[PDB]
Every structure is written in structure tokens, then in C-alpha cells.
Image (cartoon, rainbow, N blue to C red; front, top):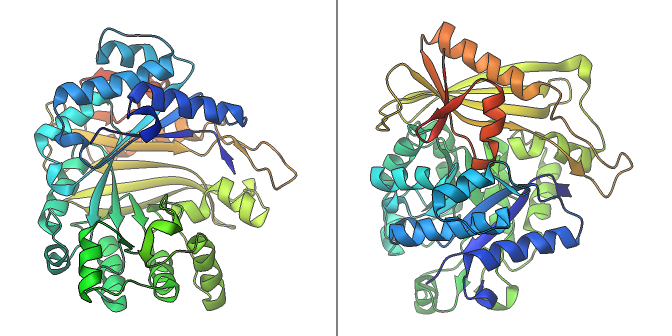
Length: 426
């Protein structure tokens, strides 16, 4: 399926073909997507490596600047100028995701990520059990994950967890309990999870453990059982990544090698009667592609679900066909717990995300182009968020975490730049 948002994933320096040049990587991906008719007016930029927040600030600012230069199609004098230019460019950076180790997620680093324009942070959690983390000689603790998650949430950012079932020392039941805990213990409650079973790749510590007879990775059966469980209990407010990996099968010494693990999980869940209600399974574009149906307007409602997370309250607002369970748009509103950013006080509510599922060329059906943007759903969710913030929680200002290329949208709704955010006085 072709999405309206182009994902541009780039690699930082210690990809290979361009010597890790940020501009060349970004440009090459955009041109490659244009070659196949994919829209590139909206770009999600993903910074891969996991060590980016530990690099020199000089390097971080330059790297992001040059990615934006490629989107803007012109040179700039500074990061700030490239960001300003990009607000009205032909290729707008609507989201910026930074991958990082949980222990590289201090207040100082979060300040830097906000300066860069980040909207999402993916934590290399892997496991929530310190026994497993220490056994595999990982460089972080679950305490690091818990603290990073709270600091990110209280700064308005989206939080994703990379999780690895089947690590040394774990078990099917241990993995299942981990997923239950991540969605029902307020220390965690991520917005998004990226799941793939632990693999044995030559040259890693996991390879050494495997060589010694300390590690037998999951085969397909076990991975399917764990991931199927995880999806069956995922809350409606959790977004999941397409189950896959960019690692070719010839480098996998041991572990799951087949390329359709996601499809195998789907068929397993069908066989067992396991339903999935998370964002990816219910979003309008995915439902049309998988099941050939569209939202029934007689049954579209504004729905609300609250949960406790990182000491505060998350409000998940959505427009949904509640007869067919099809998700059209959603907004993540947070009453923060212990913020540190200068622009967030105890009378502030945070809009951490607004997403209206938009254009999408489903090549395999007959209704070619389908979209729910420009129909009012985004504006209606914002109005409801403002009402809740003011009337129910007594807040006086609301701050939106906005992609660089989305600021203009919030300006139309009366918001103005407040530090790193778009803000409105209630």
C-alpha cells in the first residue's frame, strides 16, 4: 500500500553507498520514492543508529540541517534557517523520529532533540527485566527506560519501544508477561512498539552466547505464539510497526529467517480467534486493504479512553466507526506529571500527537484514492481537546508537539510558537 507520508530513514556516521552523507541519503530516498509515484510532500524523517543523542551537538545540528536542506532543495546558513524554510517547502518534514538507547535520554538530550524538531523518540528497551539486560550485557536498565519514558511524556513527545522477544534468559511465559506489564503498568505505557524476535548475527555478543551454548533463539512457532499474544492484548491506543526486519536471511546464523512473520501471526490469530484492536489493525487504510470496507458514517463517533502513564493522565481521543471498529483519526492529550521544560507549567495540557489518516493509493482494490483529511476530523479533535483541557482539568494553556512542516496547520487554528511548541492560551 502507498501512504501519503513518505518515510525517509537515514543513517548516521560510525547508507554505505553515500558515505553516510545526510543530504545525499535524504535526497536519494525522495527521488527513489518519486520514481515509483509515491507522494513526498509529507516526510517522516527517521534517524537510525541509536547513538545519535550521544554525538556532538555540532554533528547533530549539522546532520538534521542537511536532511532538511535536501527536502528544501536549497542550502541554508543554519539549522534554524533550514527548519524555517521547511515549514513551507515542497517536501515538508511532518515528523522526526530519533532512535536512542534508554540511558542516552537525559533532560539535556531531550532539550537537544526538541531543538532539532523531534516529535517521536524510539527507546532501545529490548527487555524490561534487568536479569536479561545484564545477561546480554546491554548498556541500560529498566529504571533507565522508566525514567526516559516519563521525561519524554512530560515533554510532549511520542514514545516508542523496540522490544525483542526470545532474548537469552527469557521464555515464552516471561515474554507474554512483559507485554502485559508494558500495557498495564503506568511505568511504561508506550505509544508505539516495534517487536521482532531476538536473532543471532555473527560478530555480536548474542553470537558469542550462541556459540557457547547459552542461547537458543526462538523459531517461527515460538515467535508467532508470543507476538500473537502481544497483539491480542494491545490496547486501542498502541500503534505497532509492520512486523519485519531489514536484515537479510544470509546474515542470520540462527533465529527466525522467513520474511512473512507478520502474515504468519495474522493467520495464527485467525485460527485461534484472537482479535487485534490496536491502531494499525483498525486504521481506515489498513481495514480497506485487508477487508475491503470503509467507515459507515451513520456510526462514526468521537470516542475517549483515559489511562494513567508516567505519573500523569493520558487522554486518547479518536473518531471511529464503532459498528465496524474502524479508526479515522486520533489525538493524544496528556496532563503532565513532572515536566521540566520552561514552557510547561502546572496549568498546561499537552497535545502529544494529532493524526488524521489521509490519502492512500490501495493498488489492490477498486476505489483507488481514499482520504479523511480536510473533512474536519482534525479540527474537531483539537476543539474537544481544548474543551477537556479547560473545562475538565482547569488548564489555561495547551501546547502542541508539532512537526516542523505541520506548524502552519496549527497556526490556522490560532496557535503560535511557544519555545519548541505551538501553543494557545485557553
